[PDB]
Image (cartoon, rainbow over all chains, first blue to last red):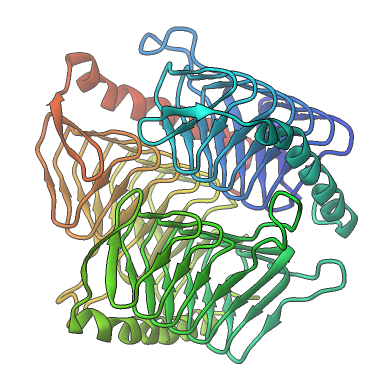
Length: 181
Length: 180
Length: 181
């Protein structure tokens, strides 16, 4: 089992009841909060910078989460910071960005260096959020580049917590199957 | 652990199915005869069922999933894929229906409830919106995917030629023992 | 360990100090130059045609590199040829194309059959380079389909070698961790 890998003396720190599929790859300076889930063939690579993920957040199949090293081309680099109750859809590409709490990241979407996604935002599937772009709390964004479509509805606001909740129940089923061992 | 039982349900594999040892298939998934699932593809039939027809390829890095039934999506969305379908590399299929003799372009995305009819081409990189029905005999391209042109006779023949080529190719990969 | 696989009597040829993550999959008729690096969950499938990659080139997480077999639909097929100091971003999709030296291929970009990317070109993240498209040296290309945006800057010119060199150093660290075994 080499899904959770120590890198230069730094071991990923996992909260309680974290699911990491045996086929996922997590490396180095990464923290995941309680009840997080990392699904088949996802990569979370915290080698050249740090990665911090909150509680009850899913990183779905085929997603890649990475960072940008500090250099003269990017002074200070770009770590990756992700909040609680975030649903990261299949095949997402998250790079050096900041994501708040209660956020839906659509499958196949891409969030780039220095981008900031505020609380309670929906990023539609396939969207591209450009470097340094700020997504305003309470809105749906769509397209390449991602543009504000409309405010979220009350049903959608509810879904942030319910949907993350469903993935918590699901990862508990996968944990019961022993898919992380 | 490329073919995993989930809550007592084991994937059902037809005759001569190739599943690369690096792919991940979970739960309520049925694959027809001569299907192939290529390196690092995921077919996750946990919250709903997935059915794939005969002579269909699911190429490298593709992810196939479904939507669970709730008040938000009453009944949910299973994933149904027909025969002689070529699902290109890094495709994203979610709770949709695909007919027979269909090309799904590499890096394309087919969303919940969409239906691709027989003999359709979805161009590489295209996104087929939720609920959209793609008309038989046409090429769809773009984000969002739009009808661009009718397929050509040579393209029509390619559905079958190409699926056949992948059948012969997966037999070579099986012969190398890549599924074990 | 089945990351580097013989196929129909042909084994991948690896140069000096090459890193292949244990979770990547390399098949058949593939050659990698000195100091190349292939990152978690990448696929390089040289079954129906040849794939050649030069020195100090990275193939990043979740990328898929493949080719097109020779047939009446594609006379002679399309092999995959990649030069030195090429940075292939996460989740790239390279199919049957030719890529020169000192090239940045953005994450999630797609380069298709018969495309030719000249030396010192930047392909922006998420771009699709159409089949047969020629990318002229010294320019930035962006979009779907990819179009010329502007010439590269001097800092961008220097980054091809800097960035590739940074990945050579990074892969030595990953080798030191034994991630390829």
